[PDB]
Image (tube, coloured by chain):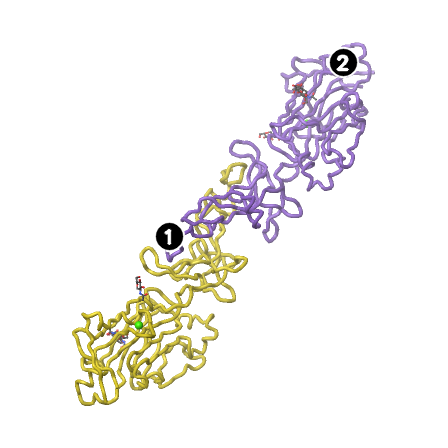
Chain colours: A yellow, B purple
Amino acid sequence: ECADEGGRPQRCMPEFVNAAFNVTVVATNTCGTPPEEYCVQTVTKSCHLCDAGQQHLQHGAAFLTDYNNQADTTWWQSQTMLAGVQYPNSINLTLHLGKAFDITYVRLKFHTSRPESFAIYKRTREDGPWIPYQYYSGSCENTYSKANRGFIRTGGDEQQALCTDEFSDISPLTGGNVAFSTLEGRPSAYNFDNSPVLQEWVTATDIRVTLNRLNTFGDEVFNEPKVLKSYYYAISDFAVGGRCKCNGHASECVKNEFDKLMCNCKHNTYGVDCEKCLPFFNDRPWRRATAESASECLPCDCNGRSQECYFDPELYRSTGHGGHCTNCRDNTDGAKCERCRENFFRLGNTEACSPA
Amino acid sequence: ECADEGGRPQRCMPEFVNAAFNVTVVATNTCGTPPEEYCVQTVTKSCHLCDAGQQHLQHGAAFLTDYNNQADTTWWQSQTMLAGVQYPNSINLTLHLGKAFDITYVRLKFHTSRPESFAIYKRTREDGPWIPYQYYSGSCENTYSKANRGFIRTGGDEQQALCTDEFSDISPLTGGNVAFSTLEGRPSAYNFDNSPVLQEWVTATDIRVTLNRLNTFGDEVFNEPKVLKSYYYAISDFAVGGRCKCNGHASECVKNEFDKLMCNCKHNTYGVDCEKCLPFFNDRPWRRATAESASECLPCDCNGRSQECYFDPELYRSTGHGGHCTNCRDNTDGAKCERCRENFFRLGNTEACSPA
Ligand SMILES: *[C@@H]1O[C@H](CO)[C@@H](O[C@@H]2O[C@H](CO)[C@@H](O[C@@H]3O[C@H](CO)[C@@H](O)[C@H](O)[C@@H]3O)[C@H](O)[C@H]2NC(C)=O)[C@H](O)[C@H]1NC(C)=O
Ligand SMILES: *[C@@H]1O[C@H](CO)[C@@H](O[C@@H]2O[C@H](CO)[C@@H](O[C@@H]3O[C@H](CO)[C@@H](O)[C@H](O)[C@@H]3O)[C@H](O)[C@H]2NC(C)=O)[C@H](O)[C@H]1NC(C)=O
Ligand SMILES: *[C@@H]1O[C@H](CO)[C@@H](O)[C@H](O)[C@H]1NC(C)=O
Ligand SMILES: *[C@@H]1O[C@H](CO)[C@@H](O)[C@H](O)[C@H]1NC(C)=O
Ligand SMILES: [Ca+2]
Ligand SMILES: [Ca+2]
């Protein structure tokens, strides 16, 4: 896993996944309460019923992160225009990953016409604020006060959210697929392994999609009931691929005693994301492991006297190592318990440095 | 001391000394009890008195290891022939060093005519038997059933005691000096640093000199009282040079709490003679430090979990190191506490490997 043939240490990481699967997404809007009528879009119009009570017509948020059977799908649906959605009213889908992940992409399978405008936000820590990841809209400048298909200029801020209309046309009344790719278009993505900026940009504990506006044909110009019952959001699969974040100090994440997902921190690191050196392993500062060298926390010396030490920066600057031992057993002094305390000596058979 | 410029470890040893100085030698015979009369040898004969009570005529064993003032001396004296000494009766002088030394030489300053025959024995450990170091006699074969001036043949037993008459002639009625040199004449003395045989041959906790026979002029052929009172043993200084044994793992010996002399064991060794690895430092076997490489006990790993380990030979054979850790704290397993016990993992913030 996190070590080579000879057994030397080396950078690792869990395998790529879709952190969404199983995760019960939360949506603000969900047709079915109370029962209402929707009508697929085309003439003709084969209308049906969104009903929460019956298991054959339910369309909860749940149908977003369940298995994807290309044969017959499962989707979540919004109340129809008639219920008062369209715009400015919006609908939200929040994916709670419960643990920081290194996100690569967020792809959506729309069971109806993709939205006219929608954005996709993320938090880097369950504390932190909702950050704009990407904006999709046929009216970027007007809807998101943002350029049509802006590109990130070199040198410029690698973390701004862009906007495009490329995915907002209605064209495919169904199967409308949308895919967000974090490092896509970031002038540094090549040097990613040494771009803290991007290394954080891909970081994410939670992801959110905001349906801001429905794409429309024009029929709803005159409040015809039968037409409104024809426009709504419907998603057949919410998939976000990336891999559990561990900084290259683990190759597998696992739920613990408290049922919260975490990293199996190798390289002598610990912490939820293996972002820190286990105490005692403070010979040098903690680092993300690269391909070049798989940074790993090195142990203190102490010579067995102390089982505890802190990281002394000055010591580190002077000598190569900076692991400073604390409270050395057997009246043995020194930065790494390597000497007898003044006026004490090592005298035969007795294990501890004894007085004069 | 026991480390070079850069501070790397290196072979050391206390400084050369005369382990005899101050040490109260013990002699079986000592004129003065009761008062008797001795007469220096030449005619004339200026006789005097050996008396225990008066401090101006006492000649205790003590005058053997006291400072040597070339101006006026101090010596220990035996009862005169008349008291019944000569031969076969012998007299003994036992130097108790109280701590194993690496002996180079034993030299004697005789205040009278050196003995006709005497040997010098040593023990390598206060337990062990009295071993013959050297034999001096004008009649080697007859007195010590040993060759006149035998030499050690190459390949042969490097530890046998030789004999010579070279120092038993009476010639100098006084100032007769005799010097024993351990490595002298030993075909291996050149390669000494890699000759356990010789390395032990020079080892010695105690030294003993045996006065077997007095050299005589012939006058005592007829029991004349005045002549017998003229023959006796008298030594002006007993000096044994060498250095406190520590195997090159110390550069100074010091008396401890119990007032018994010992080594200040560096190189991570301990024991009275630094002949063994402090527990925990069992990555490899203990060794005497040579000039080539200053063998030093290397520490076990354990990764801070255990503060105790034993030396596993098999481990040592398989991998370079063989320090095997015992009872690893924090349910952490492995030869050097480098892994979570089966069905246990390293999960964030918690220091110990916790269950599934
Ligand atoms: C659906 O997702 C969007 C995106 O986060 C949520 O909208 C956000 O809602 C909060 C509170 O309603 C807004 O915060 C407010 O910000 C303004 C100015 O920044 C400030 O004056 C307020 O004190 C407050 O902090 C946030 O701006 C807003 N984001 C955007 C761009 O609309 C929305 O709440 C989610 N669905 C829900 C729960 O309705
Ligand atoms: C002065 O130094 C000499 C040298 O050690 C002492 O002589 C040794 O004395 C012991 C006991 O008197 C002898 O041990 C005996 O050995 C024989 C055979 O090896 C054995 O039959 C006995 O059971 C016992 O073990 C030892 O041989 C002898 N050494 C020699 C070569 O004479 C002497 O005792 C010292 N001065 C004293 C205390 O009289
Ligand atoms: C959701 O969680 C349950 C229980 O942990 C699990 O059995 C189920 O497979 C999960 N659903 C998905 C989409 O994997
Ligand atoms: C003998 O021991 C005493 C007390 O330790 C010391 O003062 C004295 O100098 C010693 N004698 C010699 C010969 O050094
Ligand atoms: Ca689905
Ligand atoms: Ca003297």
Find residue A209 and report its image quarter. Answer: bottom left
Q: Nearer the viewer, residue A163 or B117?
A: A163
At x 76% / y 10%, what residue is drawn? B225
The answer for which chain carries disc 2 is: B
Q: Nearer the viewer, residue B46 or B110?
A: B110
Dot 2: element: helix
Q: Nearer the viewer, residue A155 or A187?
A: A187
> Which residue position is annotated with label 1?
B354
Q: Is residue A22 above or below residue B94?
A: below
Q: Position of residue A98 (x, y in %)?
A: 32, 64
Mark yes or no: residue A140 visible: no
The answer for which chain carries disc 1 is: B
Q: Quadrant of the C terminus of chain B?
A: bottom left
Determine crowd level at label 2: few under 14, some 14-19, many 20+ residues with C-alpha closer than 10 A: many
Q: Amino acid at mark 2?
A: Leu
At x 30% / y 81%, what residue is drawn? A174
At x 51% / y 45%, what residue is drawn? B324
Q: CA distance from mark 1 to mark 2?
A: 91 Å
Dots 1 and 2 on the same chain: yes
Image quarter where ligand 1 lies: bottom left
At x 24% / y 71%, what residue is drawn? A60
Q: Residue farthest to the right?
A: B43
Q: Is residue B229 above or below residue B160?
A: above
Q: Amino acid at mark 1?
A: Ser
Q: Position of residue A132 (x, y in %)?
A: 33, 76
Find residue B145 and report its image quarter. Answer: top right
Would you say A298 lies left or right of B135 here?
Answer: left
> Which residue position is annotated with label 2?
B228
Camera-near label (1 vs 2) is 1
Dot 1: element: strand
